[PDB]
Length: 217
Ligand SMILES: Nc1ncnc2c1ncn2[C@@H]1O[C@H](COP(=O)(O)OP(=O)(O)OP(=O)(O)OP(=O)(O)OP(=O)(O)OC[C@H]2O[C@@H](n3cnc4c(N)ncnc43)[C@H](O)[C@@H]2O)[C@@H](O)[C@H]1O
Ligand SMILES: [Zn+2]
Image 1: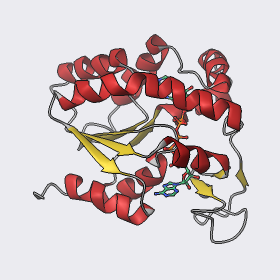
Image 2: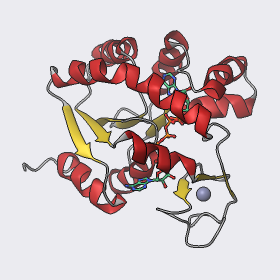
Image 3: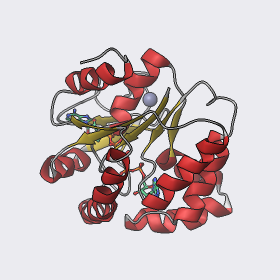
């Protein structure tokens, strides 16, 4: 289906994304991941993006919408898709509506994973990423089976440069600044669903599953 996983930095979007892909096998589209790739590719876009990313600020809308416009217009998204960490602003939200309006489609579910700020901060403090697949772990709450090695590919784990305290507080503030309105936009569009993310990973997924697995509740 056409899904959108939103939530503040550290809400467990990627974490829950890996589980949603397994089951339904829908294309995981993460703007955070795409920018990170452009950067690793060394593109001009990646150079300009990193500047904002390092600071913890949003990458300008026009650039962000642009890359999402291109990625979603690809064939591996006709049967469905899982946007992750997008949109984050109202312009992004509308640009996404029109984009799909042309393809004769629409967003069908906006899953908003909610967690209090303090938990969000603890989650980003001791987090680690797999050098090989991008997946994350948490030294305390969700450690890898074997220290420093990804459970999927044995890849090395590392801390995101921006997962430091200063940047984290700026990241949380900037993104929240856009939330309330973005949440209303979707709620008045009858597609939003809040979900308690302040629980075990498995349990947060079941709450997500209920909506994806259609069947009433
Ligand atoms: N649309 C857009 N517009 C403008 N700019 C944009 C943009 N999109 C991206 N950008 C730019 O790119 C930058 C980086 O983007 P991005 O990579 O998307 O950064 P982010 O916003 O900080 O979000 P995260 O992916 O890091 O968090 P997440 O919720 O997936 O967390 P995770 O699952 O690891 O979970 C966190 C930790 O918690 C643990 N965890 C997960 N679930 C649980 C649970 N249930 N209980 C306890 N711990 C848990 C995990 O193990 C992990 O260690 C942005 O700051 C911005 O500059
Ligand atoms: Zn990995």
